[PDB]
Image 1 (spheres, rainbow over the protein chains, first blue to last red):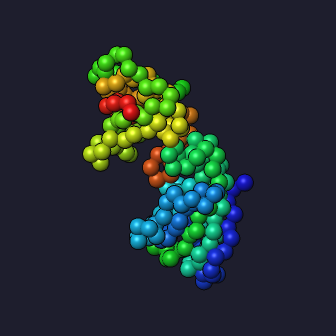
Image 2: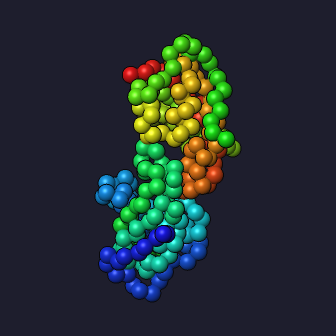
Image 3: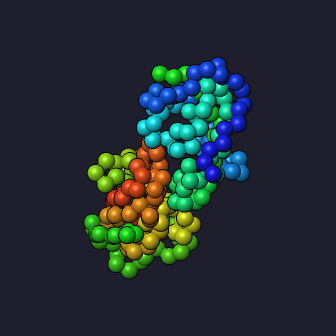
Length: 108
Length: 108
């Protein structure tokens, strides 16, 4: 099923992350029931990752690439695009669909 | 391939974790190249988990059950018994075999 991107608030509509750019984001990740399992907002520190390096789940690689700079969006990511059958025991159950609220602050 | 348990130092040879008991352990987890990705020792705080609850990877569920109280052992865990194809991007690569040094301190 992959990743579905639903907007929360608009970006510039013009600047989209390209391979090798560093995306600077704030995010919150929730299980399908709404339980938060991770958030950069609760650390008060944006998270950075390089697009295409696979240092985030596939749903982020392909979903954040669809966002424009400044946009906030909800990414609903099916387990094949997340942590799969094994999940991450103690944090993410097996076969978990995840929901992330992501704001793309800037590209570096 | 599952989990292989190789001893490091002996336990009592008599008391093995049973379903529903809380295992109190110190551990270090390494990727196959030896890079440490997690350790309760570096937090100076033992880790507790309940056997059979799937709050640890399958290799722990089935490998720690083979340890006796007081034993320290090396668990080599193939990806199917760990984090599988997806891994945990940014921490555990896809299809990673992991090595844990685990000491079973006590059962609660």
